[PDB]
Image (tube, coloured by chain):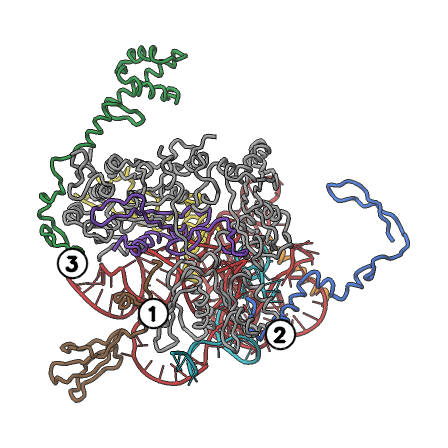
Chain colours: A orange, B blue, C brown, F yellow, G purple, H green, J cyan, K red
Amino acid sequence: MREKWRKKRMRRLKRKRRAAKK
Amino acid sequence: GKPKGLCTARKLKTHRQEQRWNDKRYKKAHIGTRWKSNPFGGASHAKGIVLEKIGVEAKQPNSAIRKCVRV
Amino acid sequence: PLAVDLLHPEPQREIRCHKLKRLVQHPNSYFMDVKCSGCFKISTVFSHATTVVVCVGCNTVLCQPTRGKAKLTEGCSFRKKQ
Amino acid sequence: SGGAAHSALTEEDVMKLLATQAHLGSTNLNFQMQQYVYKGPNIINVKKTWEKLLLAARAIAAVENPADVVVVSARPYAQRALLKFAAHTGATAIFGRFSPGCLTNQIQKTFKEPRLLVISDPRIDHQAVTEASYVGVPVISFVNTESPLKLIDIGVPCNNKGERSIGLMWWMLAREILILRGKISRQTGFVLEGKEIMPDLYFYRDP
Amino acid sequence: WTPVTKLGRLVKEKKITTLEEIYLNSLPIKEFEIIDALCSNLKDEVLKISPVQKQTTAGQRTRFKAFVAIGDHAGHVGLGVKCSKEVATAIRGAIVAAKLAVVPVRRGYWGNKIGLPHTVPCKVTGKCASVMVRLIPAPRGTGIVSAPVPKKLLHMAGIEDCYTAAKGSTATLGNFAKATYAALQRTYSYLTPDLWKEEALEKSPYQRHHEYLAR
Amino acid sequence: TFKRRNHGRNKKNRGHVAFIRCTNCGRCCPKDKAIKKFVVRNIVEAAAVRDIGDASAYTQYALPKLYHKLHYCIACAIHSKVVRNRSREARRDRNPPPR
Amino acid sequence: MQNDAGQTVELYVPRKCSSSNRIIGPKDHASVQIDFVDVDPETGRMIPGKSTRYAICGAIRRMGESDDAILRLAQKDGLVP
Amino acid sequence: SRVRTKTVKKASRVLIEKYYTRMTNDFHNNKRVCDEVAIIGSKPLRNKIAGYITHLMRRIERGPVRGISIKLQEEERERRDNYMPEISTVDPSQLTSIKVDTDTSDMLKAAGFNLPNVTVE
Amino acid sequence: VRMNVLADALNAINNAEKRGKRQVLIRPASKVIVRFLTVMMKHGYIGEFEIVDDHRAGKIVVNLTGRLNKASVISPRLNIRLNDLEKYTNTLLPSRQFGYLILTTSAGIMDHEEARRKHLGGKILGFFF
RNA sequence: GCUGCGGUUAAAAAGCUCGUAGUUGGAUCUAGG
RNA sequence: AUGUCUUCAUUAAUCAAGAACGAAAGUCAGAGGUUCGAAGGCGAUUAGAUACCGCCCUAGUUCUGACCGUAAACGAUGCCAUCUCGCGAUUCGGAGGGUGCCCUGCCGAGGAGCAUCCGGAAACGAAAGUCUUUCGGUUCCGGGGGUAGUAUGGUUGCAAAG
């Protein structure tokens, strides 16, 4: 539960980047 | 383990070339953007003009202000 | 032991060794003349027979297949062949 | 042994073995003791026992100074046998616990420099075997069918687990050492200064 | 000096006069006076003194470890290590340990067998933890192609010409020296064809000079 | 560092083992890993067997027993002291402790 | 080892195990050298000063084959039938 | 408390070993003999030694005590060791009807033996 | 799948020698194995060996003299010329005084000394010392 | 790192299997005198 | 797997690309909805408590038909062949005896355990051994720590994402 939350954070950031680029 | 057959020269050479790209030195020297990224463009010396002067806080545990100039 | 005669192994060991791991391979099976009380016809039969060997005209079952050596029917004796 | 008929196994000698049950080794067997076993308990080969006993006797006699031969045992049954063997053969005896460092610690006042070491049981006296392995001291040992032969030079197959067989085997070793030394002879028997050395002397007596 | 062992008694009585019989019979040596008496040309050197610390309740307890290499430059070399509270005592104990650990080294020829042996008989590899040292024969005049630490040990052992290949954490002085020591002492354990000839076992010194020992 | 040769379980020749719910905490633990104990006890405590016997309505009545197979997860087992931590050497000892 | 113009300039020739023919190192302390006294068949007394020497290396001794190795060596030399 | 230190224990052991004859079961007697046989620098120490000596004597009377060598006890032990019966229990005279199992199949035959006394069960 | 009977045989010999055994059994035999063992015999690194026939590849039983440090196979069978024979020997053998490098030439199977004397190259087979 | 590295825990065995290209493939033909 | 004096006769091992299967969660459609239960809402505890604890519960958890293709998917150890030790137990089949059970230092095939050469930085490993004495065949992977499995491009997917 330390790097898994980093993965979750990065996934949220990637989702936001996808929404912005779209 | 690595291949050892008498007719595996292609595989050995191709694998070695492929894995050379995972080497920091080889990649640094053959990447292709070295000239564009390096300020001196591959030279040893360069000339410039002064703009301002700054003091940089030396890293811990050293305490001092090193006196550099922006060129 | 360090000194073991591999060339001439002990016969008891050779008998109690796996058929493929002997100095020279040899099957553990054999052919036998089966004699069944009655028609008294000697019939050659394989020890580990997998089919049901039948009398020629005597028309009776001599052996029954199993997982190992064939099981001779009751009342039938057998003698190994050289 | 020796390729001679005068040193062969004698009728009464083999008799004593069956009398004392010195041929019934334990039900566990060692691949290194496959040799001294003829076909519950495992019955050992009396001829091989005799030959190994003679070989051990010759090895011990090779030590011209009897004190240098050291006999070590910790089994309670073997204390009488060890004391009698030491007295008769002029050897040195170690009873009970073997203090670690006898053979490796030169500063110890218990320090000894045996030229030859004899053991009642390798497993019981494992410490002595390990210590001898540091100074290169040859080891003879009374070993049962399941005993380990690691670092054992001459293993005399016998029933060292028994109550009476151990005493009989120690008595036989002393007898052959003295026979081959000249203090006694086969015909006269085990006698010194006119006193009959009887196996029951070595046999274990319960207090 | 009052010997406390049979070997020491024999050496003091001069019934054993060279280290060669001791090595032949594989008799353990437990008194450095034996080596002192049987090798009068030994010279020693302190390879390194390094402090080691043990954490305790009231700080760190510091003891110094000394590595010493002794040799005669004529085929006998030994390596000792001693850790003690003081550098002087550590050095003395390391010298004693090296003396007790002195071991024989076999020399050989690279090509033509003319003159005295100068190099190792064959390629010999020694190891200690991670440091592995391989000694390879070299022709005359080559010198010792090696790092300083193995070079010192080879000089003490008397090898004049030798190539070296060292691998692992060679910065560990102790392990480097011990690997070199193991490689050097492998020389008289490697079985080459010239030692195939069967020899006859002779009486050990204990067997031969037993009269004085008993007396 | 690997603490145990068996990796804290009893799983050999097996891919997946169904789990059990710990008797105390309720946590899911693999059946091989969970510590099991079979407790057979008198239905009445030793201090009241005599009272129940004297109050019995029958000349000779055998008092029944409770049989419970309890599974504990590692945490609750340690907390309840069904098992204890052992030295490095004593960890390899597999014989059940004296009862 | 022979070398030079025919001279031997080895420090010493090491012993070899009587059973496996392996060199016995100067620091092989698990090796042993057993001696058996010679006996004349009839009287059964040791001949003074006469013995047979056997050396067994530490590797074999530790492997536990020293027993059988000594027995086989004695059988070869006739000390045992 | 009342645990005797190694000093007292060693002194008592040495005194018992060297002057067993003078050591009786009486504390006053042990104190007196200690006074003349040992130079002890403290009266409490002397009394502790005497008390432990009496305690040790009480056990010596019951039986041998490890760490203490007593002349008479060792004579008794060596007599028990030297005990030797009139005739061997393994003499062929006594060995008459020994019951042996089938091990005789060849163990006592290929060896070249035909023991009359052995009886195969 | 077995692909180098010689490699397996030399591995078995090496293991037996390290364990100190007096005889070792080599599974499927072959002419190459026989010639390798014959060269080792001529050079005295093994005792006599007996080829057990069983109407198949057969077996060998070799007597070990306890004199072999190592017997190894070089795979694949590289081509060695007379000019680099010296380099290969210096690379593979412990010393110039002993140890042999086995080649397979047209003249047959020999050691590097015989190959040099006859001025022959060929394919490398293995080495022992 | 072909000679010549490493992949349980330090970086590194694909979740597992089938499979084309590639790579590698058991013993056996004239030995002797 | 075992048994086989049955048949073919090299037909084999490993495998870029390619393909099947692939826990749980998750998505789509249709049935079911007991239990438990993300999210949600309350009662507690706390300085706060968007938590641990308790109560009521929605998706889900179940089935059918399709997607995704990821797990500490672990033995953190690729597959095939071979050699090196001891002991006694265990599952399956066989052989020989005795009365389903017992015996055979019985034979193979598994799955382990403790006596273990050698190996390893060590922990430890009958393999992680038979390697500077390197070299049986073959596939994949690593090259100081981060930036970062991120940006960009490509591709698959309904999406999440791979």
Q: Position of residue D110 (x, y in %)?
A: 38, 33
From the image, tell me which residue sits under label 1: C21
From the image, tell me which residue sits under label 3: H105
Distance CA(mark 3)–CA(mark 2): 73 Å
Label 2 and label 1 in one chain: no
Task: Say if D30 sits above or below B15 in the image.
Answer: above
Q: Nearer the viewer, residue D65 or K94?
A: D65
Task: Say if B71 sits above or below B59 in the image.
Answer: below
The reply, left or right, for residue K3 in relation to residue D201 is right
Q: Secondary structure at mark 1?
A: loop
Q: Nearer the viewer, residue G44 or G17?
A: G44
Q: Secondary structure at mark 3?
A: helix
Say which chain tag 1 marks.
C
Q: Nearer the viewer, residue F64 or G54?
A: G54
Q: Residues within 10 Å of mark 1 (few under 14, many from 20)?
A: few
Residue type, label 1: Lys
Task: Say if H54 sits above or below B40 in the image.
Answer: above
Q: In which image quadrant can residue K28 be found?
A: bottom right
Say which chain tag 2 marks.
B
Q: Is residue F59 visible?
A: yes
Distance CA(mark 2)–CA(mark 1): 42 Å
- Identity of the residue drawn at 59% across and 67% down: I86
The reply, left or right, for residue K143 in relation to residue J28 is right
Residue type, label 2: Arg
From the image, tell me which residue sits under label 2: B10
Q: Quadrant of the C terminus of chain E?
A: top left
Q: Residues within 10 Å of mark 3 (few under 14, many from 20)?
A: few
Query: Which-is-in-front pick, marks 3 and 2?
Result: 3
Residue type, label 3: Ser
